[PDB]
Length: 300
Ligand SMILES: CO[C@H]1C[C@H](O[C@H]2[C@H](C)[C@@H](O[C@@H]3O[C@H](C)C[C@H](N(C)C)[C@H]3O)[C@@H](C)C[C@]3(CO3)C(=O)[C@H](C)[C@@H](O)[C@@H](C)[C@@H](C)OC(=O)[C@@H]2C)O[C@@H](C)[C@@H]1O
Ligand SMILES: Nc1nc2c(ncn2[C@@H]2O[C@H](CO)[C@@H](O)[C@H]2O)c(=O)[nH]1
Image (tube, rainbow, N blue to C red; front, top):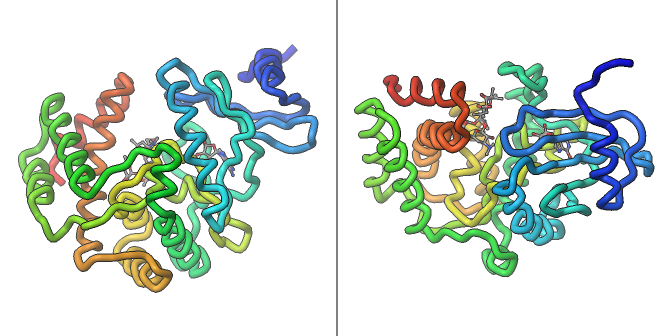
């Protein structure tokens, strides 16, 4: 007998209650704070992703995300998870076998690999994919019950998050001033909102073996909001040169821009410290909290 991390009999029973018969190899990622993620082989010979909510508060988010993905499926020129099972105890979809655009071993803080800076096929196809996403009509998002933020509501959300961090943590004075100046800088903010992925970075983008964007995953944060939300992580990974290329092609592909978009994306990236701190706070995880407090107290 060999102790294994996965509980195959419990997983089998869970999947079977939702019409999936597990058979063959599986792998398990238990490091998620909200979900256990298992990639399992099913009697169709195919791999499926089992996205297992850990708690009632997580389970509550399944049905609204299911409506998002159902709406998006025909309206994007790339794949998204096909949640053929979606309920409080289990989400399951056939695995999208294409690689993520960043490969990282669970537990590790350093990726094995990220799609290269000089990959023109990746850069170009990410920009067009993003323009396509941001072209999904607002009416479709409303009809699907999505969270909608007008430009005023988008800016208010940022203000609320900044204020919550200020109430719970002690933040470097210059950091605070940066965020406030940004919130007060009318010219930075867009006068429209779009359907955004909300958690978009190389780890949630799938690519075919030519490095062309073929899919996106992990849509929990999707909503109608500030377009720049989906561009900040591109700046973080690919730098100002990568952002410059993105904006040129995004605009050429029909994406709507505004003159201070590049600036606004950089401010959104800085605002990532707020998002991280609130995640840490809401998680109750002391390691995340220690990192967050250190970041917030530090000079940029
Ligand atoms: C938009 O700007 C981003 C910039 C940066 O975005 C992050 C990323 C994506 C964050 O994840 C996001 O963290 C938030 C809190 C929740 C979110 N979702 C689960 C909901 C999650 O995906 C990280 C904090 C994940 C984390 C903690 O495990 C790590 O420490 C790992 C090692 C992480 O550094 C890397 C693999 C590097 C190579 O990735 C990047 O820098 C991207 C660009 O960190 C953010 C918090 C900002 O929001
Ligand atoms: N290639 C690929 N990875 C996935 C898929 N679903 C989940 N993952 C991985 O599991 C994590 C949790 O959803 C993601 O960040 C990916 O690393 C998928 O359909 N295809």
